View 1 (cartoon, rainbow, N blue to C red):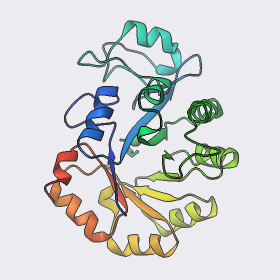
View 2: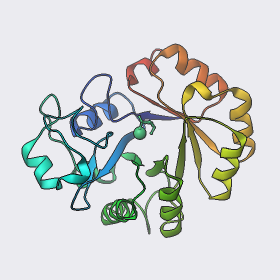
View 3: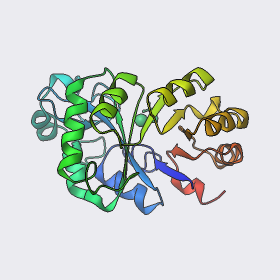
Amino acid sequence: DFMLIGHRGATGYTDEHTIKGYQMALDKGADYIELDLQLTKDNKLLCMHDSTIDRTTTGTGKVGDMTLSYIQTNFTSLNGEPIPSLDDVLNHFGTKVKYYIETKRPFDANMDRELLTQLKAKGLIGIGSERFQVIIQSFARESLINIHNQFSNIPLAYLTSTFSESEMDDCLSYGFYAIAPKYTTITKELVDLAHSKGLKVHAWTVNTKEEMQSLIQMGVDGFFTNYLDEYKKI
Ligand SMILES: O=P(O)(O)OC[C@H](O)CO
Ligand SMILES: [Ca+2]
């Protein structure tokens, strides 16, 4: 009844968005590994939070300006792990793990298409797939609506830095499964209102046991954390 999400893998303990980090998240008790995706010049999907590789890799530049091959052959994560593609992660873990996958902005129909192509190739969506094995999240309503039009049974989470009744109503209108608000905007009254509308609430990004306890008392259905070991201390 509660979803513990490893934010970019196990970010508090190791490099974000590495297969080593995704594995560490699973080892530390995450229900879901969380991927952020950026579109390469050749319309492949890179596990990368920022539009640019400058902060987290040995390289620089916009992901959209380089081919997947150029990025993976020339650069590594800060501490030397490979920079994984969506394909690399799905090939590594297959149907053994649950994925919480963000389409980063700007909205791009090519990103949505490539995401659905890679998931379908592993049987993670469409016929015979387990509901909740993949949740897709975005700040871009356009990405979630486009995906919902193509694969109506994938649970979708709308990412927001606010938590208003108008946003909950939009989630209902477009058939989204969850609203995913910044955790400091959440109150028990707002969670109860979301629940009354048939929405789940997935809070991000909570990093202390005290703040985890507060969110659980408010009745959130899940949260994203950098520090999975803190959940075992609640
Ligand atoms: O860390 P960000 O910037 O992707 O913020 C959203 C949370 O990670 C939940 O996807
Ligand atoms: Ca994210």
